[PDB]
Length: 159
Image (cartoon, rainbow, N blue to C red; front, side, top):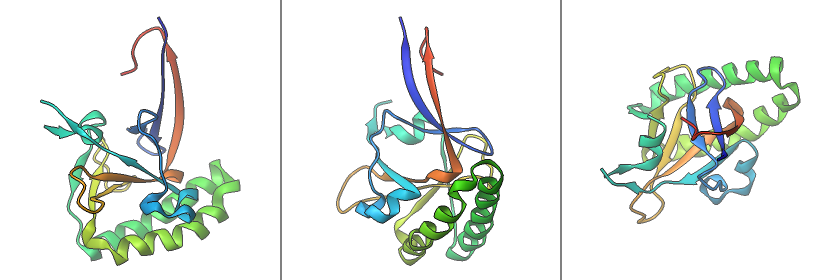
């Protein structure tokens, strides 16, 4: 029996933070944002918890708007640096397309919750989540250039 799954890992910690079990969508329904980020819908998982958070062992962290600004600046440079070395064809697109995205987050700062990976590394990728309208479960947003994809085809379930 063969098992298939594509996972998404932080390029610094290698933590799994998402999978292809979750359909991707434009962050905040903004097509322009899709170039450097993607959004997925979470659901309730019974003993209830959020499937995304539970499945990938994420942990919510508290940011003040100032603390986050400090973080995101360093992280963007950290990721851009990574791109220069590992994926240079993404360097300018990342820098360019991230501007409106980060501003939208800051501008709507109070709407967001923030999560760390299993490594709890405050220097790595932060997973964003917010509630759309009156929806009961949150939606999670990922900065995709801080991630890499890894396909798995095993004779046992992936863990």
